[PDB]
Length: 279
Ligand SMILES: Cc1cc2nc3c(=O)[nH]c(=O)nc-3n(C[C@H](O)[C@H](O)[C@H](O)COP(=O)(O)OP(=O)(O)OC[C@H]3O[C@@H](n4cnc5c(N)ncnc54)[C@H](O)[C@@H]3O)c2cc1C
Ligand SMILES: CC(=O)Nc1c(F)cccc1F
Image 1 (cartoon, protein in one colour):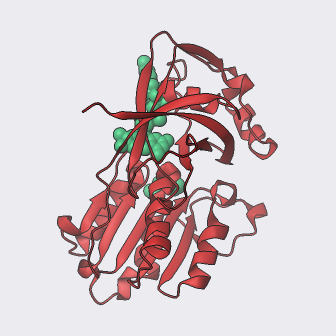
Image 2 (cartoon, rainbow, N blue to C red):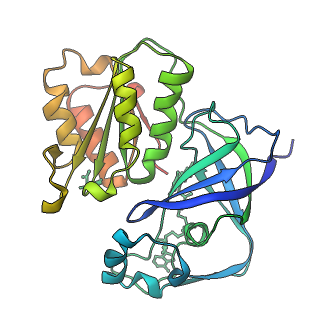
């Protein structure tokens, strides 16, 4: 049973943070990609050569791209390849597949390594380009219980976080207690926050919190600071009567995943109540 494919057209490919783009694809009209929240597709690329200098990076992120000389990078692949990306839209957002794609630059200590293949290709895409996706696939799925849900996200982990949370509130009309905790470095790295604030106004059982590890003075930030595992503990789990009765859904960078899961285990949360997507 061959995997299904769709040739989609790029609607938009906008930065949402210094190093994350929202790639929004139009599904062919009259077609459906029958995915579940937390699920993903694979993208393919043809052979290509792309220059970071040709990327469309909005001006508020350019001084950091210039600082790290990122516009000098070039990426070339001579054979097609495939990679997985998680849906940021939820299943009732029809007609589109929306992705959050981190640019996978070379390691700081090995700066002359090749850039990441598929993320560099994706950042080269412009409105009207065509891309082939396949699947959908999934395993990062919500448990269907009445337990309280705690979503913890970082970086491009925002995509399955958004999909799950909108799926619970808008498709399932869930009455469960749900909260979302997102760690980012500074205010310009935060996105979709207006959507989550509106969901929290409309859904008394839902709350949303951002921690900034290194806010800039000009962020004028009076919110939580530091790492999200500490903020989640200090502002919520420390006087929760039974954190072990919560379901925790984690998708962030590895240093986040490790710190959150360690903090949860220290509280006595069982592995079966911790679901991780480690990209
Ligand atoms: C189920 C699943 C879902 C995912 N969902 C998402 C998502 O929603 N968003 C997202 O951004 N990603 C997601 N990922 C990750 C994604 O699939 C890719 O792994 C990611 O985009 C990086 O792939 P790439 O082709 O750009 O880089 P690759 O070509 O795989 O390279 C990876 C890294 O290795 C470095 N490298 C290469 N050669 C060398 C070398 N010689 N020395 C040192 N370093 C080297 C590259 O510079 C790059 O940093 C998901 C992964 C899975 C499995
Ligand atoms: C440990 C940790 O959470 N670090 C971190 C950060 F400080 C900013 C953004 C993402 C992160 F994972």
